[PDB]
């Protein structure tokens, strides 16, 4: 009589719809640091699952660009038992001197979305593959190429 | 002080004579620092209005 029965399915698509404050303070893209809340504007937490059914905390950080108007920088981090390791986007157009790669969001003057990642889809690097990420996720024997 | 307005002239009978020497009255961009010495803090709105 198992206490848990099911077939775990790994997370592959995450759809997020948010409204960003237009009157929020501007921030410096090059000074972003997920350990310092004052470098960015907002942070949300989401839960993701690996292939074997382990729960992980995915914290999303939003930064308002100061150089470019109506432009937002978004960063991803994966939380494991050793700490919070940042997640890098392969082709994201938001880059920091610390090596954390996010994606840029541009908006029109009427409040609608203008562009995402210079028109390219948002694909993140493999979570548990040390060859692809400088901060690999310790997936505890699960699929490292997720 | 650099404050630029427009002049309104009227005849002797009180009717309108001329506005801004016959040119249309359009203001500089509200939130654009490149064209206005005192740009409006538009809080993310269109600065070129």
Image (spheres, coloured by chain):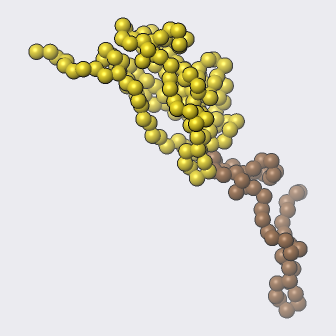
Q: Residue at x 44, y 14 (%)?
A: A145
Residue A64 visible? The answer is: no
Res A96 visible: yes
- Of A94 and A26, nearer the camera is A94
Q: What residue is at 36 percent from the left and 7 percent from the top?
A: A141
Q: Is residue A40 above or below residue A23?
A: above
What x and y, as percent, mark residue A52?
31, 14
Q: Residue at x 75, y 55 (%)?
A: B29
* Residue A120 percent across, percent down from the top left: 56, 33
Left or right: A54 as drawn, with respect to A98: left
Residue A54 in percent (x, y) is at 33, 16
Q: Colour of chain B?
A: brown
Q: Residue furthest left?
A: A1
Q: Is residue A78 left or right of residue A34?
A: left
Q: Is residue A47 left or right of residue A90?
A: left
| B25 lies above or below A106 | below
Quick one: quadrant of the N terminus of chain A?
top left
Q: Quadrant of residue A38?
A: top right
Quarter of the view holding residue A92: top right
Of residues B20 and A100, the one drawn nearer to the viewer in this rendering:
A100
Q: Quadrant of the C terminus of chain A?
A: top left
**What percent of the width, then of the height, locates residue A5?**
19, 19
**Residue located 80% across and 52% down the image:** B36
In the rendered image of the structure, the colour used to display chain A is yellow
Left or right: residue A48 versus residue B48 is: left
Please tell me whether residue A97 is drawn above or below residue B31 in the rendered image: above
Residue at the extreme bottom: B13
């Amino acid at each position: 009589i198992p206490a848990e029965f099911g077939k775990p399915k790994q997370t592959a698509n995450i759809e997020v719809g948010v409204n960003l404050p237009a009157n929020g303070d501007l921030k410096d893209p090059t000074q972003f640091d997920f350990s310092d809340p004052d470098t960015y504007n907002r942070s949300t937490s989401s839960t993701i699952y690996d292939s074997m059914g382990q729960s992980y905390k995915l914290t999303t950080y939003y930064l308002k660009d100061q150089t470019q108007p109506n432009t937002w920088n978004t960063y991803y981090t994966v939380t494991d038992k050793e700490g919070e390791k940042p997640l890098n986007v392969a082709a994201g157009d938001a880059q920091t001197p610390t090596g954390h790669v996010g994606h840029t969001m541009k908006f029109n003057n009427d409040g609608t979305l203008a562009s995402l990642n210079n028109g390219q889809p948002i694909t993140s690097v493999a979570l548990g593959d040390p060859a692809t990420n400088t901060t690999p996720v310790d997936m505890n024997g699960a699929d490292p190429a997720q």
